[PDB]
Length: 473
Length: 11
Ligand SMILES: OC[C@H]1O[C@H](O[C@H]2[C@H](O)[C@@H](O)[C@@H](O)O[C@@H]2CO)[C@H](O)[C@@H](O)[C@@H]1O
Ligand SMILES: *[C@@H]1O[C@H](CO)[C@@H](O)[C@H](O)[C@H]1NC(C)=O
Ligand SMILES: *[C@@H]1O[C@H](CO)[C@@H](O)[C@H](O)[C@H]1NC(C)=O
Ligand SMILES: *[C@@H]1O[C@H](CO)[C@@H](O)[C@H](O)[C@H]1NC(C)=O
Image (cartoon, rainbow over all chains, first blue to last red; front, side, top):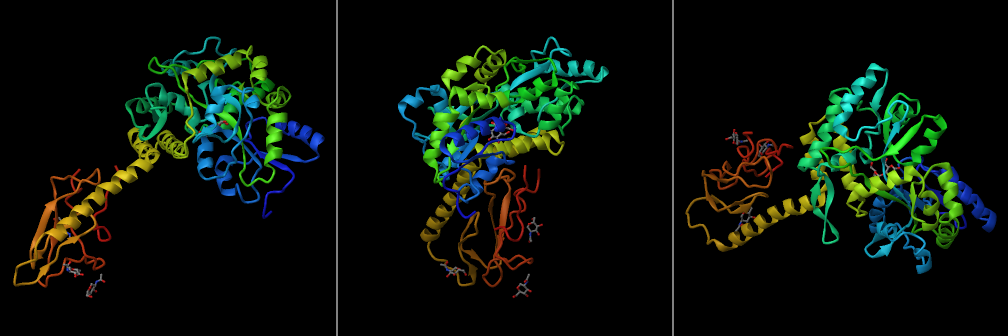
């Protein structure tokens, strides 16, 4: 396919969500209009979408949590959606706020997602209120052939409540805008959260390999007392007939766990030629009591954005927990910088869990990565400011007055050097561009007997010796 | 702590 088929809807949604429910709504749409809706669930659709979106294998509509949609907008991959005020009043104002980017709506919200603590009531009538009291619990449970707690370690969505509990954050939220120069991935509290998790692994209470489906199997087969997961999971648990509760997440250092809250949302592809059909599907078929029930029946959405349908669902205690955990947490930012933050934290947790890096090492890399935008400007500007002084002083100092050869004034890339006489070894303090450079130590540059700067014997390149700058640590 | 290089090919 060179282009997206005009006159059908192709829809993309994650494989843990109610995709067969959605296809049912799609079947009703085809009954009324005559146009086929195809629902799909590719792997890593959130990563595939930018690459394929305008290509012709791209979907007409994409479902994902709201955090990825700012980056999608910046890349111009999404249509602006145009619901009138009457439709807007059908959803809660806070949900519309998650899908607003630079003043425009960029997706239709569907549901508010937050992880909760799930537990096996038969094994555990009384769930722990606190993370610190878990290892104790796992010791008892191992004696009885069980594990206390198994959940996805591979994805940082699941480990972020712990990290944020004692003071970790993504980007500082001041003035009603997120400040990307200030990142809370390497602070005291984050270090503390991740350390607790790594210690659970050192003391055998969890296994670093644990991923989404291992942990699901363990809970649903009654091998583990507890799990951490969202409303989508509840279907498969029902099926198993494990007797289960959904409750508040455990406190760490007396502060509650703070999940990042996702608003599952639907965007329309900018390259779709079926945009009004898409709008009609989403507004008149999907976001209805009828429609959301088809989806929630297959796999639960949690707390929905549609006020009418949330009023059916609000009596359910699993929803109340979900909202309680949401309230303790934070609504995700949608800025483009979120893709970098998740990569950072994902990478850190895996490396540390895995044994590859200490916690302080793993996280310092996350801070470097999560805040790449800002650190490139500063690093870059340090250097440029030095270049310009060099250039000014190269223009200002009068000509060499010396009857012999001399190497002339130059900017070497890191430091300024003056006209220097033949056979003279010139020196000055190391620059402070890099964290491993001691500016009490010095740099040499030798001018040869013929008035030419020293060249490296490895490649005859003009070269100043910065070896003392970082040689002692 | 990634280690800064000072060899030929730097300044
Ligand atoms: O783990 C990083 C991941 O977190 C969030 O994705 C969640 C998504 O919100 C949920 O709908 C659920 O299905 O699981 C995902 C995690 O496995 C962010 O929305 C996402 O962008 C980020 O990569
Ligand atoms: C200095 O040396 C450079 C490089 O050999 C040369 O191109 C330039 O003409 C010399 N004169 C001045 C004032 O820089
Ligand atoms: C450096 O330059 C000199 C003169 O051209 C030559 O003798 C020597 O082979 C060169 N070394 C390298 C590393 O190419
Ligand atoms: C640079 O200085 C160091 C330390 O003084 C010395 O060992 C080294 O030989 C110098 N580098 C070269 C290639 O001349």
